[PDB]
Image 1 (cartoon, rainbow, N blue to C red):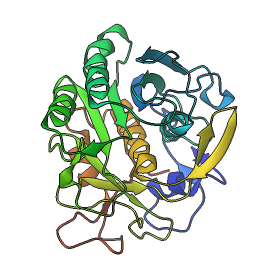
Image 2 (image 1 turned 180 degrees about the vertical axis):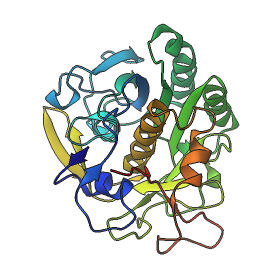
Image 3 (image 1 turned 90 degrees about the horizontal axis):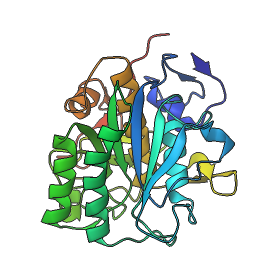
Image 4 (image 1 turned 60 degrees about the horizontal axis):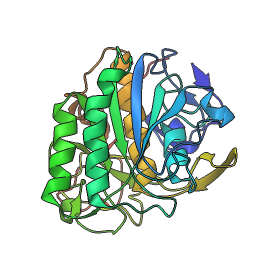
Length: 279
């Protein structure tokens, strides 16, 4: 399948070169997979989600996304126009308040929630969790992400936006999950992207158009935007049967575009997420 005039990041993940604008992908499109977006919530009524999104848990007075961040990330995973995996099922877990903040204890509870809640959902092709959040190093936060991964969920986490080594941030620094840095449309490391040996992969993160609250759209930047590209890619590849939740991060690294990014510090992987789709 071909989506013309796609957001640059979608075109990038199906291309061996920057500078194109059509997204190519297998029409299975993540059908039968599920992606949990652990964030500020999801505006499930947005026409872009087509009834495939739902809130399943909140720790606050509402499950609605009063911020936009979680809706944007969910749109990059799975919206019809802005999403990588256009037929996946999206489940929102609101661990962040409408200012975008959350206590680590709540975030940990949300991760353990997903590890159990997947057993209440129909995801025959597999389960992914997208975590566009983080703060300073916490062994307890890292352990929660490790448990979620161990339970059979492909965990993708943001590297962080400090232009610093991600070893000092959580859950970015957890070795067993997929830690995602950000790149721009010219294949440069995004100016804010964290780096370091703990990164597994880069995805598009600068000037990413996606869904927003109020039935709208906007372009924003962050490792928060790169992470759902990778989460959606994992769901798409799992639906194709090419990999599993336990092996998808490594598979994405195996099949990435290699050595094409600029300003990658010595010792950080130079790997850009790529779907290897042959139309």
